[PDB]
Amino acid sequence: EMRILMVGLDAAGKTTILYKLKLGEIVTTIPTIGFNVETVEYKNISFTVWDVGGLDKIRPLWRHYFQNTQGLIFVVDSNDRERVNEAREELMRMLAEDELRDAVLLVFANKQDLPNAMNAAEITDKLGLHSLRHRNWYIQATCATSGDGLYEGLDWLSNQL
Amino acid sequence: FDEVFCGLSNEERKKVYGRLFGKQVLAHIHSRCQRDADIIREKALRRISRECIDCALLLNKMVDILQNARLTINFNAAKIDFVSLLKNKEYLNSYAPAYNVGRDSVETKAFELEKLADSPYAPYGQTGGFSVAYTPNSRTFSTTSRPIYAALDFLNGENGGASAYGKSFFELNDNVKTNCTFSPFDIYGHRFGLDTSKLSTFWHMENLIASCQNDFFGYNCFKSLVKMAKDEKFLAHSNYGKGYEGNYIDAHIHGDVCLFRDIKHVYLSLQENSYSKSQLYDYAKQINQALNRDCIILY
Ligand SMILES: NC(=O)c1ccc[n+]([C@@H]2O[C@H](COP(=O)([O-])OP(=O)(O)OC[C@H]3O[C@@H](n4cnc5c(N)ncnc54)[C@H](O)[C@@H]3O)[C@@H](O)[C@H]2O)c1
Ligand SMILES: Nc1nc2c(ncn2[C@@H]2O[C@H](COP(=O)(O)OP(=O)(O)O)[C@@H](O)[C@H]2O)c(=O)[nH]1
Ligand SMILES: [Mg+2]
């Protein structure tokens, strides 16, 4: 088993990524008022993924799970250029948590099917991943609609286990 | 991607579609509270000034208390086998029983489930009537589409938030409350009256404050929450949690409750249990060492 906290800005594609891995379908947009949780069996590994709607206003409520948080999947809307730096700041706040210092970071450059979407390199530069230290991270260009890149990121998490 | 995807059995798809319906029920109640946010706050501040100073500060203190309250599911360890319950690795509602039919009708009228009839997950959240055995006629109706009931124990009761259902109780993790709707009275009672406007989410406790009871006898919910906000310590009323209409804040967990993933503590009563002291201490020590937590707490 591996416990994954899927976080990021809203409308990035967190819920869609979760239920595309779980159902293989594209679920309708359900405003995540609380949180979703699904277990996905992949390569004999049970990924329990917590899709947190928005812990920006409920940070202490989730610190109970931080101690057993093995992976962090940060989904960023690669087409939302006006908010890419906002995602960086939220990512920095997630990485400054002492209870998540031993967790791996998987960045999903989501919505790559859009024409104006930044590639994985441009997202890596705007989020500041190359300036991180003592953090086993990785970025993957994904498209939750078609499903590309989803299993590539899960393969990376499986190796870090 | 499609090549790699293993697939899902229908019973698993059925559970997920149910959970997706429940999240829409919560999103429906949350949108209702966002629409009436102004009138709810004005009504709540009206009650505070009616009892009692900066009402904005006192209201925030009462909201922070209700949000930071613990979520409890009480049970009777002498009438049900908790060992069989814990080994199931999951908590289930009553749909998994002639009361279910009426409970479906209450849930349909209280949560406005007819407003979701056009949803793509409606076939998994609608019973489609009940058969002669009080079983849903719809072969696709999912248990996960209906909430799991709990109590918001904001006073830290000696026997939980709803001791009327047993001296033992599960204490769920705090994040579970974010998936909950809240009511000042049990939704199956007359004081609730199937009033959807009395339902609030985790982000609109002001509705729960303006709608809670202020009875002139017995346990008083409004005065208890007011005194706790004013940093006054007191013993909770002896009927706290006992009584379905008005003696506890009813919570509806929209989502599954897994054991022991979503469980912080399990308070097993020693004086109300079908097992002996030595057996209960063995179960506690055994489960605790297996999870490396202090989950099972005997008392
Ligand atoms: N019990 C509480 O803490 C609580 C809190 C607030 C309101 N209420 C109200 O009280 C009503 C009745 O409460 P109640 O506890 O008497 O009945 P219930 O509605 O909880 O009945 C469900 C029964 O199924 C059992 N069960 C749960 N998971 C199971 C599993 N995996 N396998 C087998 N059995 C399983 C439960 O322990 C219980 O005996 C609720 O419908 C609700 O409206 C209850
Ligand atoms: N084109 C495209 N759209 C996406 C993708 N992922 C999500 N979306 C859209 O984003 C909208 C909301 O995304 P959502 O899953 O709610 O993001 P979340 O709020 O962060 O969980 C949906 O209407 C989807 O159509 C993607 O990979 N490509
Ligand atoms: Mg969302």
Image (tube, coloured by chain):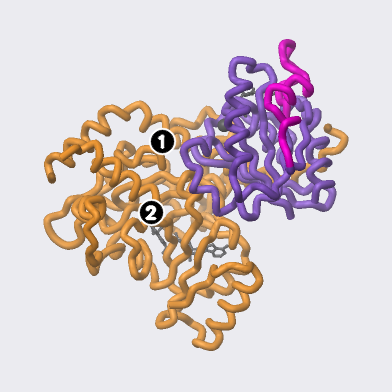
- Labels 2 & 1 near each other (Cβ < 8 A): no
User: As displayed, is residue A28 above or below residue A122?
Assistant: below
Which residue has dot 2 on it?
B69
- Name the mark nearer the viewer: 2 or 1: 2
Amino acid type of disc 2?
A: Ala
Residue A134 as seen in the image, left or right of residue B295: right
Other residues around mark 1 within 10 Å, as few (<14) / some (14–19) / many (≥20): many
- The picture places residue B186, in percent across and down from the top left corner, at 33, 52
As drawn, the chain in orange is: B
Amino acid type of disc 1?
A: Ile
Q: Earlier in the sequence, mark 2 or mark 1?
A: 1
Quadrant of the rendered structure where residue B283 is? bottom right
> Foreground: B124 or A94?
A94
Q: Is residue A110 magenta?
A: yes
Quadrant of the rendered structure where residue B209 is? top left
What chain letter is assigned to the residue under label 1? Answer: B
What span is in magenta?
Answer: A108-133
Q: Is ligand 1 within 8 Å of the beta carbon of the residue shown at mark 2? A: no
Q: In the rendering, which numbered label is found on residue A124? A: none
> Foreground: A39 or B166?
A39
What residue appears at the point 37 percent right and 46 percent down from the top-left corner?
B182
Which residue has dot 1 on it?
B29
Discs 2, 1: same chain? yes
- The picture places residue B199, in percent across and down from the top left corner, at 35, 41
Quadrant of the rendered structure where residue B74 is? bottom left
- The picture places residue B113, in percent across and down from the top left corner, at 45, 37
Tag 2's secondary structure? loop
Tag 1's secondary structure? helix
